[PDB]
Amino acid sequence: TSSIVHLCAISLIRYWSITQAIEYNLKRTPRR
């Protein structure tokens, strides 16, 4: 089972470029 988290992590990273710009992007022009 711990073998999953293994690939998971990697995957996540490879798919890290999504969270950062998940909401903010939606409502462009963040910050007051």
Image (cartoon, rainbow, N blue to C red):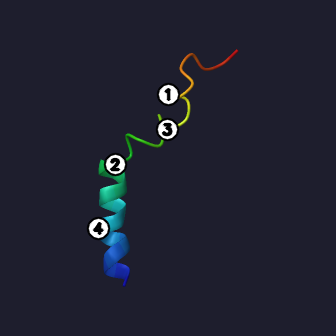
Classify mark 1: residues with Cα within 10 Å, few (<14), some (14-19) or many (20+): few
Q: Is residue 10 above or below residue 21?
A: below
**Residue 2: image x %, image y %?**
37, 81
**Residue 31: image x %, image y %?**
66, 19
Q: What number is the disc on residue 8?
A: none
Classify mark 2: residues with Cα within 10 Å, few (<14), some (14-19) or many (20+): few
- Comes first in the chain, label 4 or label 1: 4
Location of residue 8 (image quadrant): bottom left
Residue projecting furthest to the bottom: 1
Residue tagged 4 = 7
Q: Nearer the viewer, mark 1 or mark 2?
A: 1
Residue tagged 3 = 22
The amino acid marked with disc number 2 is: Tyr
Work out whether residue 14 or residue 22 is closer to the camera in this orientation and state it: 22
Q: What number is the disc on residue 15?
A: 2
- Element marked by disc 4: helix
- Comes first in the chain, label 3 or label 2: 2
Q: Residue at x 35, y 51 (%)?
A: 13
- Comes first in the chain, label 2 or label 4: 4
The reply to whether discs 1 and 3 touch (Cβ–Cβ < 8 Å) is: yes
Residue tagged 1 = 25
- Element marked by disc 2: loop
Alpha-carbon span between mark 3 and mark 2: 12 Å
Alpha-carbon span between mark 1 and mark 3: 6 Å
Classify mark 4: residues with Cα within 10 Å, few (<14), some (14-19) or many (20+): few
The reply to whether discs 3 and 2 touch (Cβ–Cβ < 8 Å) is: no
Alpha-carbon span between mark 4 and mark 3: 22 Å
Q: Is residue 28 above or below residue 22?
A: above
The amino acid marked with disc number 4 is: Leu
The reply to whether discs 4 and 3 touch (Cβ–Cβ < 8 Å) is: no
Position of the N terminus by quadrant: bottom left
- Comes first in the chain, label 4 or label 3: 4
